[PDB]
Each structure stands twice: as C-alpha cells, then as structure tokens.
Length: 267
Length: 273
Image 1: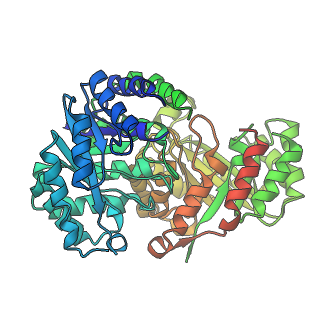
Image 2 (image 1 turned 30 degrees about the horizontal axis):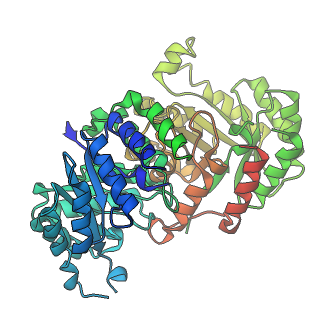
C-alpha cells in the first residue's frame, strides 16, 4: 500500500515543558510520523521546550515552525539541532488577496526561504498559505519552484475552511498533473473544519495524490479547529481495501492516547 | 434554486425528553424553517403517543411525522396520533439487506419481504405523506434495492429513505448508491430519495452533500448531529454548507440561517448535553 504520513500539530493548540514531552511521547507511541514541537523564535521558553522535545523523543521527526525569514529559520535550526530527524516548517501567502504587498514575482522570495532552511536541518516543509484561493496555474508555479529550491514537503491548505471535498480534491490533482516535479516531493493536506468537512476533505486530498495529512487530536484548534487525527486515520483504516493507504499509526492505542492528550491539555 | 427539504429528527433520535419541553423544541424547530420534523414514536408508549398529538396541536406549519414499525396495527396507531396534525407524515420501513432478511426477518426472502408495498398502502390512507426507509440500503444488493424503491413508490410512497445504517460509508461510495437509484429506478420522478447518513467516521455532513448532488432532495438530520452512537448528520452544517455554495450546488432550503446558532444553543441546553 501507499504510505501516507501523519503530521500532528497538536502541541501548538493549547502546558509546562514536560507535559509537552509527555504528550509528544504519547504521540510517538501512537505512531505519528512528524510532530511539531513549537515556535522557537517566539521566546526562550519555546526554544528551550523545542530542544527538550528533540532529546526526549527521537523516532518521529521533530518539526519547528518559523516565519519565512532567514533570522528565524537559523534560530529554528539551533533548536532542532539535537533532533535525530529534524524538519523546519515555513511558508508565505499564495492568494492574490494575500499578496496584495508584493508582486507574484517577489513572492518567489519563498525559494530563498527554502534553501536557507535546507542548509540548517534535515527536512523542509514549505506551505502555500491560502492555497485554496490561489490562481491554480500560479500555485502550480510556486510548488514547482519550492520543490526545485529543495523543499521535501509542500503543503496545500484550505485556510478558509470552506472548501467542498471534490474541490479541494481537484486542487490537489491539478497540482499532481501540473507540477513538473511533484514526484520528488510529498504534497500535504491541511483542511480546517469550518463547514465540518475537514476529515472528508483530507481524505479527498489523499485520494488525489497527497501523501501527508496535517491534523491534531480531536481536531483541536483555532476558530473551528483543524482535521481530527483520530477521524482521518480511523477512516483510512476502515477502507484500506478501497483506498489503499497505510499510516504507521498504532490504531489500538488510538483511543486512550487520544484521551490522554485531550485531558492533559484540558480539551 | 432547487429545493432541498430538511427533515429533522432531533425530537426522536435525540431521545434524551419531556412533553412540555418537546413542544418548545418542536416550535423552535418550526420557527427555524424545517420542512418536516419527526415528532416521535407513538407505539413506544402512551406518553410518546400523547406527546405527538400535543405537538401536532401546537405546531402546524411544517409537516409532523411519526416513526413506526411496519405492523399495520402500529401504523393505524401512528395515524391516530397524527389525526389533528395539519400535514401528517408516517415514516416506516423494512430491512433491505440479504443479511437482514436471511438473518433477522428470517421468515422472509427478497420476495415475501415485499410486504412493504403492503405497509405503504395501509399507511398511505391514514396520513397525508408516507416516507419509507429501505433500511441498511448501503449493504443491500443495488439491483434489488432498485426494485424495492420502484415497488414502494408504485405503492404510493412519497419519500424513500436510503440510510447508511452502518455509518461507515465514504462520501463518493454513498454518492453512487444514490446516483444508481436515480439512474435505475423507473419511477423516481414520481418521488424523492432522502439521505440519512450516520457520523461514525465523522463523514455524515459530507455524505449528505454527496447524496444531494446525485438526486436526494430531502435530508434527515438533527440539531448538533445528536443521535445513537456517533449520532447522525448535523443540521447546521449541511444547511450552512449548501448556503456557502449556492452558486455551485444551486440548492436552497427553507431554513432561516439567522436562527441556526441560537436555536441550537437552546435545543442543546434543553437536553442538558
């Protein structure tokens, strides 16, 4: 079967500097592939908690979030420095709405961000913010560019959280069929649940070529929350025969580990 | 705009109530723009029976519906509880699976099992509308499921329910099950399929939409998605998803969105959950 990777972002949705380790461990044991440890540039405490995650947990690859700015990327690099398998996670707008202040040209100031990041960590995931509302041909150009720049994973979010399944699905497929190099890189889904269609949307992206799903336990999150890790994963498992995807998740420990995080973070 | 009917079941499926409170939920449901609100299960007990009649006397705009076992006695009781209701509807049905008929209904086979045409004619004389669910339609032989729908409509059936009883169906899988029926049921024009999806995989809302994009013109749902197990399709969601895409789905309902949020917070509190 085709392996689909799970990128849990549930730690950035609230915890002291050891309850985060306990949660991150629970996540490691549940079988997530990438767990986002934090936002290192914000404060010494977040930096310190990120390096602390990279010492306690090492099987899954540890990710840190940072703005598309050389200064931040390098600091993020200092914090992930002890990670067995590290990864930075950055991005910049792709919608005309967003771009408007640059020019669709100067936006390629993303490539610079990627190379900068590849020089300081193992993997790099660049996300195209507001991807759902970007000129498709243009986003195609931005994905190709970021991949060429070296990005390992390019994220295509439904930032508004208002897209219908087949739509988001057609968006992924379009990139699959129009990026001249998506073969050497994993596209990732990221659907907010504003219309309550995040699980259905993430699965739609998976059925079209996306090989990574961004989610959080109980879909916890800002506004109407993100994709529910438990739902996407459990849904996939039920229709393996039809779908043909594997998650490395340890389904049994799914409920209790879910109960742990949701009760520790006090959800 | 293509009209999609909202058939609410919170008063029934969200079984956690009080005859007083029932009407309060029942009218709020009414002043929200719901086409059909299943008021209950008469047979169950005299209380539910009475509660029903008492609703049909306080709410009158939307069509009041009663859930009932095919049992003819049960059906006539249903009617009797809806006598006063302006627009009365009887919701009844039978198993659709080779699994159910062989293992639950046992005495019957695909053919005797079409004693369903029998229940639809009886019900069709005691009440205005008659919705007929082909239970476990998600697992029934599509060919036979077609014949049942064909047969139950040519028996009077105004609305045929096609519920994913398991609740583990995928958006498109279900989309086809409705598409097929629209493409293989000689007389669907003489009626309308109604979706009833369960949120076991947290895919009820999406499923209902797939259903509506393939012919279903009615949608079963509850406030907040309350119901057995993982509950069923949430009303706010579907209703607000069709609205944020009118220009693409070309679908609308007689729902007063402007009341969704509040009416949802009082139906919630009322049930304490």
